[PDB]
Image (spheres, coloured by chain):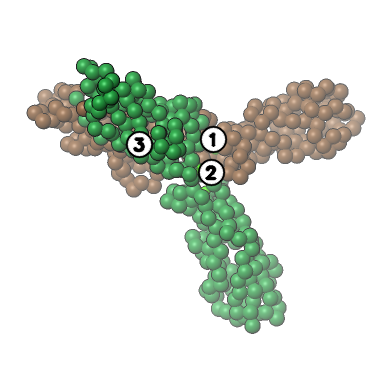
Chain colours: A brown, B green
């Protein structure tokens, strides 16, 4: 006989259900000669938040009761129990782990709308200027939460239309052209764009912020 | 002992892994007195597409080896096998279903960039004119593939800047104002927008097309 294994139960967040929705049905094969009742415990069940996951005490059917939000809780570790009439467990508790599958339901947001940095005159190419980054509430290990950066605009456009670059993963802005001269421009304004889905422009979500770089003496 | 039918296993499309990624560990309880080898069969394993799901022949650990795409294959039906070293079946094959969970990785697309329709002069409010629609490659039963429409603009702006409306669920363009007069204007140009996630404005994906409506005599 194959040995009972519960797989990870992966549920997408923001389910429309309808609810309750069946997940797994467990039972003890000791029920052939003993009378059992089943229960679930843990955060999601009997610990806060309570009642997201419930089990039918007679059938051992496990269910979800409402939509989930990975951004509140991404993982539930439940334990299911089989007990006799004395109230004693007749099986080792079984682990039921629930992973909430991430949806891309969060746009990138910048901590500040305006970021200030400076860079000295005559700085050589590759000179570090500043870091601007955004945050995406989605899962950083999924595409939904993986951010890429770029410069959409630089003003003014002299002596070179691309005085800077930004590291697409880290948000480090470094100079790439020479000719930084306070007598000619004292402040460059860059528009920074963050977009998720690893910067995919066609199905990624994006946002923008601005970086003001002062050229110092 | 616990007893439980393995439920369908849900995996998100476009997983970043890393790979290989463990899904379940299956085993026969006959391995306590026999030395067993495990295997998987079905499209996704040993049939095309090949090598997506693999099992360790000694441990019975099942794994994914690469990202999935709901838009290519949405479901895998696998069978897992237990044999002794003589090559003899020691268990009935077990069915393993894998559901590929839909991500919003597809932008709405209109069938045409330009849609042509007409409406007669002096048509009363509520006159159906035409239907313009888009398609979304994602699951039409999830938010990712559920579309809403709206009118972004109307040109020219007379006699009213809103001569029409569009059914948000359906793409049906209907007149809502009177004063349709070919002598004064023969054509209105509308920009129509489709956006998914049921038209969610902060994280829904959008696209546009134009409707040219001719006023007939
Ligand atoms: Ca969420
Ligand atoms: Ca999310
Ligand atoms: Ca996101
Ligand atoms: Ca896809
Ligand atoms: Ca999809
Ligand atoms: Ca979509």
Using the rendered image of the protein, determine whether residue B170 is visible from the camera's viewpoint: yes
Q: Are marks 3 and 2 in contact (CB under 8 Å)?
A: no
Element class at badge 1:
helix
Q: Quadrant of the N terminus of chain B?
A: top left
The residue at label 2 has a CB less than 8 Å from ligand 4: yes
**Quarter of the view holding residue A93:** top left
Q: Is residue B61 left or right of residue B115?
A: left
The numbered dot on residue B78 is: 3
- In-front residue for pair A3/B160: A3
Q: Is label 1 or label 3 in front?
A: 3
Q: Is residue A10 above or below residue A217?
A: below
Q: How many marks?
A: 3
Which residue appears at 62% of the width and 37% of the height? A199
Q: Position of residue B69 (x, y in %)?
A: 48, 40
Which residue appears at 85% of the width and 34% of the height? A160
Q: Are marks 2 and 1 in contact (CB under 8 Å)?
A: yes
Please state the chain letter of the residue tagged with numbered disc 3 in the rendered image. Answer: B
The numbered dot on residue A36 is: none
Q: Position of residue A111 (x, y in %)?
A: 62, 32
- In-front residue for pair B184/B62: B62
Q: Position of residue A195 (x, y in %)?
A: 62, 38
Element class at badge 2:
loop
Say which residue label 1 marks: A143
């Amino acid at each position: 006989d194959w040995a009972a294994v519960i797989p990870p139960i992966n549920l997408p967040e923001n389910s429309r259900g309808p609810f309750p929705q069946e997940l797994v049905r467990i039972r003890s094969d000791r029920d052939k000669n003993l009378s059992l009742r089943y229960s679930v415990t843990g955060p999601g069940a009997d610990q806060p938040p309570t009642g997201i996951f419930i089990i039918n005490p007679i059938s051992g059917q496990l269910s979800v009761t409402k939509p989930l939000d990975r951004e509140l809780i991404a993982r539930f570790h439940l334990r299911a129990h089989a007990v006799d009439i004395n109230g004693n467990q007749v099986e080792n508790p079984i682990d039921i782990v629930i992973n909430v599958i991430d949806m891309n339901d969060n746009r990138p947001e910048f901590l500040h709308q305006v970021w200030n940095g400076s860079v000295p005159e005559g700085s050589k190419p590759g000179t570090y200027v500043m870091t601007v980054t955004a945050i995406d509430a989605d899962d950083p290990n999924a595409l939904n939460g993986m951010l890429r950066y770029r410069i959409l605009s630089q003003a003014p456009s002299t002596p070179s239309p691309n005085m800077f670059t930004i590291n697409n993963e880290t948000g480090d802005i470094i100079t790439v052209a020479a000719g930084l001269d306070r007598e000619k421009v004292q402040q460059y304004t860059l528009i920074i764009q963050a977009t998720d889905m690893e910067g995919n422009p066609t199905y990624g979500l994006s946002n923008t912020a601005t970086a003001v770089i002062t050229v110092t003496d």
